[PDB]
Length: 270
Ligand SMILES: *c1ccc([N+](=O)[O-])cc1C(=O)Nc1ccccc1
Ligand SMILES: *c1ccc([N+](=O)[O-])cc1C(=O)Nc1ccccc1
Ligand SMILES: *c1ccc([N+](=O)[O-])cc1C(=O)Nc1ccccc1
Ligand SMILES: CC(C)(Oc1ccc([C@@H]2CC2(Cl)Cl)cc1)C(=O)O
Image (cartoon, rainbow, N blue to C red):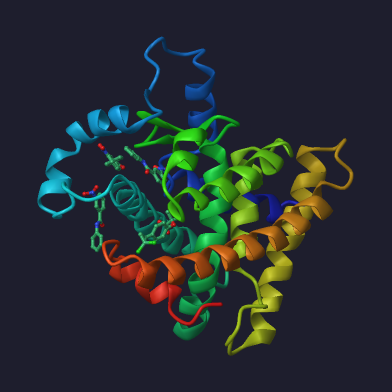
């Protein structure tokens, strides 16, 4: 249990709560509705989509996407939410003791492979069996409407709902997700890592606080730590399959222009 570790556990917790505006507590209260009778605007078909797109009429006109196919509009603003999460993650990583001290090539490498493995883990916080919160909790896209899209777009988010359902069953709080996300970033297994030895030292410190933190917060889930280690493996597989589907859609779809920042991350990944 010790004391210095508890401080580190909360440095990682105070960060995250500061960099990620949408956490599990806020999301879990919206989906519960036990704090407001003003539910979010549900998006379950093309009509509700075009309605919700009436608000964001400026972002679409200036971006030249107003008259694009429905699938290209969704996975284009949704692509904009990941560019924001990558920025927040880059700042959250600074709170990880030892990360700012590593070589820039290693920092860029760790974030290059860990951003999406964490985007999908945190994405589960705003997901249930029927949909996921969007627009900072103001909207709610249905899990079925995303499947109703034409392939391959309909095969993009369904795997995320699959992981989220099994992941959310572990019943973690932001205190646990923070350390978990920190462990994802500190992974000495990423390809091309220079000082592969030091990063392993930094990962052991985080993974150790995570094991002790889970043992202290979820005392009855003896094997919660092994379960999370398995989830880290599934996230790596989930990102691999996802990144492969972006390259496929990047050439076979002449109307879906990938974002520049995300274009560098997906380059020569898996
Ligand atoms: C993304 C796609 C479509 C819309 N829309 O039809 O309004 C909105 C968004 C979105 O993420 N908006 C947003 C902006 C700023 C902060 C939170 C959410
Ligand atoms: C980001 C947020 C919202 C929208 N939108 O719905 O108009 C678009 C974006 C965005 O980043 N679009 C984009 C795509 C490709 C290259 C640059 C910018
Ligand atoms: C896509 C990925 C992540 C989020 N998010 O968690 O804020 C949202 C979206 C998204 O596509 N939102 C959306 C779609 C359509 C209309 C409004 C908002
Ligand atoms: C997690 C998420 C939403 O996955 C995507 C989805 C769509 C795209 C864009 C449209 C093509 Cl396929 Cl060029 C890139 C990444 C993201 O990275 O923002």
